[PDB]
Image: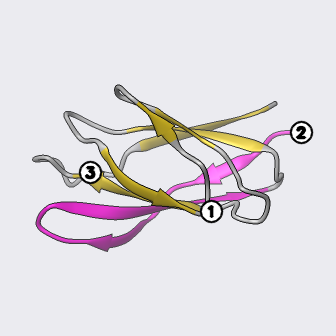
Amino acid sequence: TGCSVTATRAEEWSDGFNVTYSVSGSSAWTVNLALNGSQTIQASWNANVTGSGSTRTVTPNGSGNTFGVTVMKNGSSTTPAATCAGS
């Protein structure tokens, strides 16, 4: 009982990068995304993620263990942090 979410860099440009976190081990998992600096969430897919501060609750739609969102670099091309928990 322990989801294993992972992070990775998919697309990228002089404005933001499409991060692609891959979850494997369980379907009912939750990956709390945490942008860095003033970064923000421009878009997402493969999972219902939302929020309004420095983190967004991500969730699997049923078969999209791996999600992907546009990290608004906003002066930061570093990948965000993501953690998961069994619940």
Assess whether residue 77 is covered by the magenta stretch.
no
Where is residue 46, by image quadrant? bottom right
| Mark-to-mark CA distance, 1 and 2 | 18 Å
Q: Nearer the viewer, mark 1 or mark 3?
A: 1
Residue 15 lies, in percent from the top left, at: 14, 61
- Mark 1 = which residue? 66
Q: Residue at x 83, y 52 (%)?
A: 26
| Mark-to-mark CA distance, 1 and 3 | 19 Å
Q: Quadrant of the N terminus?
A: top right
Residue 60 lies, in percent from the top left, at: 70, 52
22 relative position to 34: left or right: right
Question: Is residue 82 shown above or below 6?
Answer: above
Question: Is residue 11 shown above or below 52?
Answer: below
Residues at circles 1 and 3 in contact by the CB criterion of under 8 Å: no
Q: Residue at x 43, y 31 (%)?
A: 55
> Mark 3: which amino acid?
Thr
Considering only order in the chain, which callout, 2 or 3, is on the residue closer to the N terminus?
2
Label 2 Cα crowd, 10 Å radius (few <14 / some 14-19 / many 20+)? few
36 relative position to 7: left or right: left
Label 3 Cα crowd, 10 Å radius (few <14 / some 14-19 / many 20+)? some
Label 1 Cα crowd, 10 Å radius (few <14 / some 14-19 / many 20+)? many
- Mark 2 = which residue? 1
Q: Residue at x 70, y 60 (%)?
A: 65
Question: Is residue 4 shown above or below 45?
Answer: above
Considering only order in the chain, which callout, 2 or 1, is on the residue closer to the N terminus?
2
Residue 78 got which mark? 3
Provide the residue span drawn in magenta: 1-24
Residue 38 got which mark? none
